[PDB]
């Protein structure tokens, strides 16, 4: 819910803070890949049991599936604190 | 010289620079997961045609793997440059 996403060119930027669970980071990037997004740059940190994550990714092809579908897909596997 | 790996107790740190290919970042992390390592923190950036990556991971269970295995396993999908 309290996670933002932005688009400029062929690139998408995701900034989210969620509750940490074992393997959640790999799952989040897997959903990003399942959304036809190739993650090139990641900045992440942990603290107080929370994981702060920023992902800069680009589309593997067309701009298909880049609006709010990321939010629903990400919320399926991550609990935004 | 090449990309280095370190181990301290149950914690592992991976820092590598490799040639950028589409989808290589998730594949490297999948290999890290294939090494029974749970990645909690990832730092990655692109530049020229190279990908610089630093991964902080923990062992997924008592099935402890070894560094030389990590070096060889990572090279299967990433070209260290």
Image: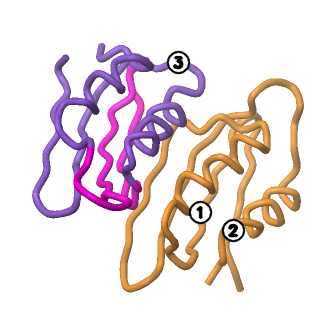
Chain colours: A purple, B orange
> Which of the labelled discs sits on residue B15, or is there none?
1
Q: Position of residue A13 (x, y in %)?
A: 22, 48
Q: If the image is split into quadrants, where does the N terminus of chain B sit?
A: bottom right
Q: CA distance from mark 1 to mark 2?
A: 6 Å
Q: Residues within 10 Å of mark 2 (few under 14, many from 20)?
A: few
Task: Tell me the residue at 87%/25% (across/down).
Answer: B62
- Let me know if marks 3 and 1 both belong to one chain: no
Quadrant where the C terminus of chain B is found in the figure = bottom right
Numbered disc 2: secondary structure: strand
For label 1, the SS is strand
Q: Main secondary structure of the magenta part?
A: strand
Residue B4 against residue A4 in the figure, above or below? below
Considering depth in this image, is A5 or A69 the residue closer to the camera? A69
- Please report the bounds of the magenta region as a residue range: A38-64
Dots 1, 2 in contact, CB < 8 A: yes
Residue A61 is covered by the magenta coloring: yes
Q: Are marks 1 and 2 on the same chain?
A: yes
In the image, residue A14 lies at what x, y percent? 25, 41
CA gap between label 2 and label 3 equals: 27 Å
Q: Residue at x 71, y 50 (%)?
A: B31
- A66 or B79: nearer the viewer: A66
Frontmost of labels 2 and 3 is 3
Q: Residue at x 17, y 20 (%)?
A: A2
Q: Secondary structure at mark 3?
A: loop
Taking depth in this image into account, of B65 and B30 the one nearest to the observer is: B30
- Residue B68 drawn above or below residue B79: above
Q: Which residue is mark 2?
A: B4
Identify which residue is drawn at 87% across, 36% down: B64
What chain does badge 2 belong to?
Answer: B
Which residue is tagged 3? A21
Contact (Cβ within 8 Å) of mark 2 with mark 3: no
């Amino acid at each position: 819910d309290n996670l933002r996403i932005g688009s400029f060119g062929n690139e998408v930027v995701i900034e989210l803070r969620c509750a940490w669970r074992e393997g959640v980071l790999l799952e989040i990037m897997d959903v990003i890949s399942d959304l036809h997004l190739d993650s090139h740059s990641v900045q992440s940190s942990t603290g107080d049991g929370l994981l702060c994550l920023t992902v800069n990714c680009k589309h593997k092809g067309s701009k298909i599936a880049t609006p709010g579908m990321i939010k629903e897909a990400l919320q399926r596997v991550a609990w935004i604190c």
